[PDB]
Length: 413
Image (tube, rainbow, N blue to C red):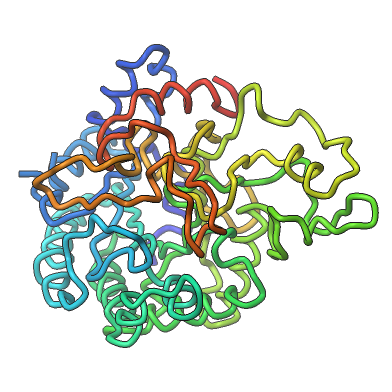
């Protein structure tokens, strides 16, 4: 069974580690009490050598005996991030066996312990930047040999299946499969195909749809929840919003429209009728002086669209430390039809990746999508990366970015 919505009638975990970095920034106390997910993005995060056990104990303490909800990100597939120029994932493409025995299994072992406390809800975010690569990045300009390999060897599909079963058996664990964002799989050509692959994964490695509680979009990304001034079917004089360089015949201009349609598609495919969707609104506020306060007046199609849209990125494929971004809507329960919650999965202020080479021992290769000077590739419309300068290694505190995110918060603080 498990509750219909693990966020409903629950307190939310506050990560003391994250909170201390937020409160330390000028004005950071205003958001230092917000709930953020704990990221298990490598084997070493499990024991922490705060480990998972440490965060879960803290969540229990914060609960006081009433329902409480902690979000844990599962993110260590073999051949991780198969389309990226560089991946920080420690597990290689042939390492599914290590994924199963040294990553999932010990996490399962810790969550099982905590099943004894009825009022703790563990929402597990399952493998970001995974399955949709096997739809969109296997052929053509932008295809990678790594993605083709992971599709051929079933490493993503079977890895994900495994996590769903192992964590899904556990009574108070609520699995959400990552579902990219509308600027990735919103097209007529990849939406259905993504749905098919989600279903494949959910039935792989002994899993069933009964181990999937829902889906999460926009995780660690910047796509708008709603675009207030843009109608995907609207027009600028005789020209459709659809034909703009921004929209590019996507079926959607925002995340909410997207996850609502996806939710219906998935149920039709054979997922449970009571699936709920999440959207990560950590960094998609797009507020501050540059935020449109109403629709453009321009007669140019692209000037109307560029001046009316709150997501101001150059291209929706720009994912790294995005310039001008702002904190989004704060974590909130059942905000819209079919959405269990808006969540802050990415903890704001933590870098997405280094903007130059920063030599390291923990195995984190320089990804040029984080480099301000990078001129792009097929996957971002061959555009500037849009990344903020002088960024630390992924997960390290990025003060310039936190101050900006904080000043650009929408709704304001």
